[PDB]
């Protein structure tokens, strides 16, 4: 009885874990691009500000 | 004497005076306009010319148009006559009820109270809202700030607070709409007439209204808060009593200033804000305060751009508050209202010698279990709760029950939730949280604790669960 | 024109995201100080004064109205971006559309969980 | 009239004229040079001086040097004598085959077709290519985004689309290489000659080539797409044809613009692109449509910066695409050519109201069965095929047959495969799959549908020997 | 005054984050071109200069001293940012506090690995 | 010289990252408009005209050749930085090196997964 | 020639000359001042006006104040007379001991040695520091750089190296205090008097001191490095004998330059730096080098702003070095000192043909087991350890041991560790790391390897830990 319960619970637990992972993956990726775009924009506005002040 | 317009760009207008230059902050009156158009002197550019900020639309202005020096800063009506009335940035009635016949006027600009005038008395102000009373209590005559991203609940909260404090208040109140929704102003106005706090037939009104909403040009929105707080300053001193000041939303002050700064010639600071951000806010906030002469209990809704609390606007505002209620988007999405972050909300009054050691210890206890749960959430995100030690499962359980017990139905939201609003007494709040921490309800289901008032309602609900 | 003559009009702004990029273009060429995502500090105001003109007039003013359906385009469902957050705080509620609901057949792809309309709910037929 | 150089700063040249100034966008001809140097007017600085962007190197220019105003924007040869030839931004032949003896010339700058000139119709531009026509059909006058760089059979797809459109529509093609690598430009030229779409002997060439090589200054790389766009407008407007315009690659069109904008001193936008990102793209893409007279259909190779589909460049391009063609290694490694991804590729006109209920239903069926097959991959892998239900087992056979029937031999590649190419008429495609889904071929082996034309060719290939 | 007259004084600057914001304001209004994060290119020198004034004097000089405890406010617990690393690179150590520890009950909320003292046991009695 | 006189040359540019930095210095000081990472709008053009000069001539031109191996230094593995982006798109292929591979024992530290040669198969002997 | 100040903005001063116009780099003396105020010519603005950077504070200056051209760049004392003395940017004594009676003076701006002057010889310089000697060994006469964010151990490492290499050293040493802590300068100075490395009574001093700390304005911090290397150059060339050159911290040269860049009228480059960062750095760094005439062993502490090694300052510095020692906050935070990052420190001499394949292989083996653990870490932090094989987890435990055996009690650090300093011979380092890799210690507990010298102490600590 035990191994049947165990293998069905590991299956279930690993289904979830895997699906959580992927979701986390999808989110971090989107967070990565937002950050990537803001750093460039941010670094560029900083250059322009300095240049315009002259 | 008269001056003439030499330049116009949006709200910024330059005016030349051949004789007698008007000092900074003076109000000028533009000639040839159908409705009063005020220009506020910002600086002396040189060559007998001044740079000013318009308090209304500049469409139709022509180079050469005459401008008059009024001889002083913008002055508005103050006193018992403002009650039940609605005014704009420059003191004009906008409720179509005729002239505000006061005996007193006051400049919307003034130096903040001096150090010797500060007060040091600390006394709690019980709101009946569990999260706030327990974790970061408000103080009588203190400064309260409500931070929140878009549509997270700032307005609902300030309204509940008006409903729970302003109504049961002996003194007067001032509500200032700054850069927000006009129809929210229409709803508020009609709601207060319905409840009688505003009366158009007698002199019993208890609230004075000041509005400069998101339909207004930058200069107006950048000054309406000064106007509102000027009305409250009068009640504070010139009557020696207790005043309530509500403002939705003070962020709009800084945003409006950001709009004109882009035209005043300033080199931009971080994120495109005006370089004077902190000092602009400082000379304004320091007037919103209790003095030894009288007290002002202020509640300011504070918008958070893109949900970023490190945004210069909000980040600079923290320094001005006695209590901070930070709303969270992630909390609201969990259905928990008010969406208050229990770990990012603070009060300068959370001190054992002020609220007592029982209250003090119960708050530290709640925050402790919430933080421990938080530290776990990372490991739960992948594997889940089933992988936790039989002990961590326990902190998780009590924590989740505590998160929901912090939630509560508001009276002011009844109209859309369909649930009777609730007001829980401070003694009942401490107790309830003590019992959860002590484990007295480990056998009750989470859902029993969500959206109720006092502890007894949680158990009852846990029963209707058959 | 209809709003002020006792009649009712509906206006769709399809879309305001693009209007905001156009205005950003005008602002940058004017050399105005760029802020978040390079939008001018007055992008909030660009849309606020606009949508404030959608209104319900009382009977003393003819009883007419102007209803507005501003459209906003997000990127990878980011409703916390600058513009979207600006407009959320202008309007009276939102109808959120979701790619996954759509890319699954649920059409219209409305996320009934997020979507809200408080002032509209009060103005709904008893039968419904 | 003739002006003089007053400033040379890299690819930016300021020219002064004493009389009438040349309008913005006019082409200027620099005098006293071995090779033709063109200058496109960008602004009117005032003081009778214009600011231009250079179409070639500026080394050797002297202040004082004479410049002629050609009186109009850049003009290039248009007409049938452009087919099989290679041209540059300014219309000069770069194939060393002599002058491009056309009867007409045309300006590369132009307003997009007017509202009334638009065609309120939506017709599919049949390609004879099964995957495309059935599942993600090209729309006449629409934009197709071609994803998947090298190694996935792009060049052959381009050549075959050319060939096919000439057969089934009498329309010609135009290849615009924006940022062409010289090495690859030489090879594309020889592959087209070898494939026949280009003929150096007779006037049967089907494609006109326009190159903006990577080593040319930003201005030329920015204008080449317009050049190739103008050549194609000739075939639509003067010969009422349905033209094909290839733009490889649309991202480099955006980068050139960004570089030109940078050089003119314009403040950069989000992520560093030109402030005019959307109008630069718009004034160009809008010229590609279906007018009353004919149509220009465009297939555009798209490079996605940092694999981020939300990056401003691809984000702006997507606003104009009507469908996409995704070419992948994964599919190429399964031997299915063309290497089109059947679920990743899509089309806006995949709607019953447009391509008809029959086409739509068949398409949707194939997609679902391909989806259902992808969903069974798990249960089959770890468990066993001899365990799927009769319904499932059958959906695996039909699906695999389906994915093979999407394969197709091309004529363009008859020199390398030895096998005859196929141009499958739409109704034949819709029906072929309809029969597979119907199950009218469940009695045949998968390999019977691999690499063939019409459904009949599947039934035949089956008979073979056994 | 104390430091040089044979006595010992203790100074607290609460806080330098806000002093840097004011410096930035005054500097930008003087039209000095902004630097990293919009601060004057010399924010470090603003603070290094000041803190070097805290010192231990020798007996020949009276043997007095001035001790300083500057305060820096971080954003989201980021000790590694620019302003914060500047000031750390000046002082003879730092006491770093985090909100997570503060809420778990660790008060004072000091993070031991990230805090340091550059004087060490030379500032302690033998007993300690 | 070799390329055009029937011979073969191999040129190595180590590295173009430093060349672009020098060109930037001169552009900023001549006060040409600054763009991404403060580079001038013609920095791409700088490298594109250099690398196109590498080529394989036909027989009529002597059959000579010139092969180029430009070198770019990335920062923290960011191949999407400006200069790197420019040179990656100019070239016919790329050999990507990685730190993690290197300290793991993989040396040369080439990522066989991403590295590419668009010329590929056509440039290798039958044996290989 | 005599000039008149026409403008003053912070450290940047504009002077007008009616007749002779002083060339870029010349030193101008300001008249009417209690103490010597020098201005260095940076640019000729036109209209007979030059732009300058001051070498000391500008408070008190007035428009119209007279300025004299010395007719040359800043010139300082060089030679045996500087030994045991402390000079400032402009070669004035700051030790209150009187004039530096040198027979020669030298300009602090000089051309760098030509390519025909370079040397390729390279030999190991053992430090006694396990991680360095093992993973990225220094070389005699080579360029060594110590990178580190704020407070991770740069200075403690340089002080330890001075203690272990410069005390024994038979030649001469130069220490340049560049924009660092004044307290550190008073520290070092008394430290050296105690060790007799500096002698105030006789003439046996073996070290010259030059200082310009963070209490000084930017002009002074931008040129003090030059001052110090100018002293070192004389020993190298006008004496040949071996020279040690320590600089804490040369980043400060680059930061100084950026403090005045906008005032000098430049458009900012990336991250707010001066467009000339690389070339400024090159013409200075190319002077810090061994040549055929003589050897210089340079050790430079290098600040890393915001803990980001991709920062232009530190990033442009890697190319001028022969051996890099990279320090990390993530490692310091764990109690691991010296906080050296074993996967980001390198040496041009880490080659089997130079150090022997035994030295090479062990170093390389240490790097592999560590990169492997590092790649593993985040995985097991989620799925736990149980899923690893007995061998996969045997590397996890040795990796942690090796990471601990890299830590070391510095002599100079006694006031921090509460431990007696330790010095480990090269052979002992290789041996020890080799044995752990081989498994000869899988039965000892981790903490036995923490903060010790030779592998014997690990065994002995383990015994002290048992009971
Ligand atoms: N206390 C609350 N109870 C229930 N719903 C709430 C509460 N506070 C906010 N909400 C929900 O969030 C919406 C936005 O609240 P509101 O105060 O108007 O947003 P903002 O923060 O922008 O001022 C409300 O219409 C309601 O749907
Ligand atoms: N090897 C070490 N052993 C023990 N503590 C150390 C060691 N190196 C640095 N520290 C601690 O960290 C502090 C900062 O190190 P320091 O060398 O001054 O940093 P920086 O790189 O900023 O110059 C030291 O004062 C000491 O407290
Ligand atoms: N101290 C040090 O190097 N000086 C002494 C150490 C003991 C032996 C004699 C020399 C260091 C200076 C920098 C900070 C840490 C201590
Ligand atoms: Mg609100
Ligand atoms: Mg140090």
Image: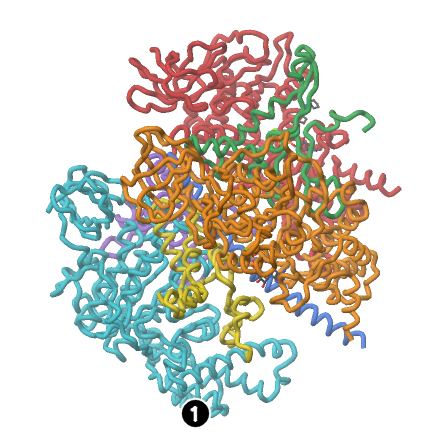
Chain colours: A blue, B orange, C yellow, D cyan, E green, F purple, G red
Task: Classify the position of the N terminus of chain B by image quarter.
Answer: top left
Which residue lies at the image location 38% right of the left edge and 52% below the top edge? C24
Ligand 1 shows up in the quarter that is bottom right
Snapshot quadrant of residue B80: top right
Q: Does the residue tagged 1 have its C-beta within 8 Å of any atom of ligand 1? A: no
Where residue G465 appears, as percent x and y from the top left, is: 84, 41
Instruction: Determine which residue is flagged by label 1.
Output: D463
Give SS at disc 1.
helix
Side of C111 where C19 appears, left or right: left
Q: Residue furthest front?
A: B202
Where residue C7 appears, as percent x and y from the top left, is: 39, 70
Q: Nearer the viewer, residue E55 or C25?
A: C25
Side of E121 where G466 appears, left or right: right
Task: Classify the position of the C terminus of chain B by image quarter.
Answer: bottom right
Binning the other alpha carbons within 10 Å of mark 1 as few (below 14), some (14 to 19) or many (20 upward) gives few
Where residue C46 appears, as percent x and y from the top left, is: 41, 54
Q: Nearer the viewer, residue F93 or B444?
A: B444
Q: Against G312, is C27 above or below?
A: below
Which residue lies at the image location 64% right of the left edge and 63% below the top edge? B334
Where residue G262 appears, as percent x and y from the top left, is: 41, 31
**Residue B14 can be seen in this image:** yes
Q: Against D410, is G62 above or below?
A: above
Snapshot quadrant of residue D381: bottom right
Q: Against B257, is G97 above or below?
A: above
**Residue G351 can be seen in this image:** no
Pointer 1 chain = D
Side of B215 where D121 appears, left or right: left
Q: Nearer the viewer, residue A27 or F26?
A: A27
């Amino acid at each position: 009885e035990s191994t049947t319960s165990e293998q069905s619970a590991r299956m279930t637990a690993m289904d979830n874990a895997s699906k959580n992972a992927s979701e986390m993956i999808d989110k971090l990726t989107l967070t990565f691009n937002r950050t990537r775009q803001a750093v460039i924009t941010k670094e560029l506005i900083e250059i322009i500000s300095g240049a315009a002040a002259l | 004497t008269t001056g003439r317009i030499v330049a116009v760009i949006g709200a910024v207008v330059d005016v030349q005076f051949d004789e007698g230059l008007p000092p900074i902050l003076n109000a000028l009156e533009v000639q040839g306009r159908e409705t009063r158009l005020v220009l506020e002197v910002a600086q002396h550019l040189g060559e007998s010319t001044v740079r000013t900020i318009a308090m209304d639309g500049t469409e139709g202005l022509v180079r050469g148009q005459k401008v008059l020096d009024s001889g002083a800063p913008i002055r508005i009506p103050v006193g018992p006559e403002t009650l039940g009335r609605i005014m704009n940035v420059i003191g004009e009635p906008i409720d179509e009820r005729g002239p505000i016949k006061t005996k007193q006027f006051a400049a919307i600009h003034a130096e903040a109270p001096e150090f010797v005038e500060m007060s040091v008395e600390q006394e709690i102000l019980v709101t009946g809202i569990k999260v706030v009373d327990l974790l970061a209590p408000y103080a009588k005559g203190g400064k309260i700030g409500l931070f929140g991203g878009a549509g997270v609940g700032k307005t609902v909260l300030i309204m509940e607070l008006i409903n729970n404090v302003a109504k049961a208040h002996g003194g007067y109140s001032v509500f200032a709409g700054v850069g927000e929704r006009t129809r929210e102003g229409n709803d508020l106005y009609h709601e207060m007439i319905e409840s009688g706090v505003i009366n158009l037939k007698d002199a019993t009104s208890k609230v004075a209204l000041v509005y400069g909403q998101m339909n207004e040009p930058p200069g107006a929105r950048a000054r309406v808060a000064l106007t509102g707080l000027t009305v409250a300053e009068y009640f504070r001193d010139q009557e020696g009593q207790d005043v309530l000041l509500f403002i939705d939303n003070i962020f709009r002050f800084t945003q409006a200033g950001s709009e004109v700064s882009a035209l005043l010639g300033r080199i931009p600071s971080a994120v495109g804000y005006q370089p004077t951000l902190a000092t602009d806010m400082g000379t304004m906030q320091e007037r919103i305060t209790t003095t030894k002469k009288g007290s002002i209990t202020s509640v300011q809704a504070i918008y958070v751009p893109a949900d970023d609390l490190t945004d210069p606007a909000p980040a600079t505002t923290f320094a001005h508050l006695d209590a901070t209620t930070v709303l969270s988007r992630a909390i609201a999405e969990l259905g928990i209202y008010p969406a208050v972050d229990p770990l990012d909300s603070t009060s300068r009054i959370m001190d054992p010698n002020i609220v007592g050691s029982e209250h003090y210890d119960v708050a530290r206890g709640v925050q402790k279990i919430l933080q421990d749960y938080k530290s776990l959430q990372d490991i739960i995100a992948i594997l889940g709760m089933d992988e936790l030690s039989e002990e961590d499962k326990l902190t998780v359980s009590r924590a989740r029950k505590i998160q929901r017990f912090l939630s509560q139905p508001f009276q002011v939201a009844e109209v859309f939730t369909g649930h009777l609003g609730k007001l829980v007494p401070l003694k009942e709040t401490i107790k309830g949280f003590q019992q959860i921490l002590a484990g007295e309800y480990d056998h009750l289901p989470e859902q029993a604790f969500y959206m109720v008032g006092p502890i007894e309602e949680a158990v009852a609900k846990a029963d209707k669960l058959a | 024109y209809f709003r002020d003559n006792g009649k009712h009009a509906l206006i769709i702004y399809d879309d305001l995201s693009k209007q905001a990029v156009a205005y950003r273009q005008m602002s940058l060429l004017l050399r105005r100080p760029p802020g978040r995502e390079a939008y001018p500090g007055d992008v909030f105001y660009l849309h606020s004064r606009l949508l404030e003109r959608a209104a319900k007039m009382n009977d003393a003013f003819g009883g007419g109205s102007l209803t507005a359906l501003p459209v906003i385009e997000t990127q990878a469902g980011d409703v916390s971006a600058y513009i979207p957050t600006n407009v959320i705080s202008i309007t009276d509620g939102q109808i959120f559309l979701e790619t996954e609901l759509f890319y699954k057949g649920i059409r219209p792809a409305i996320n009934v969980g997020l979507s809200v309309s408080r002032v509209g709910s009060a103005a709904q037929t008893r039968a419904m």
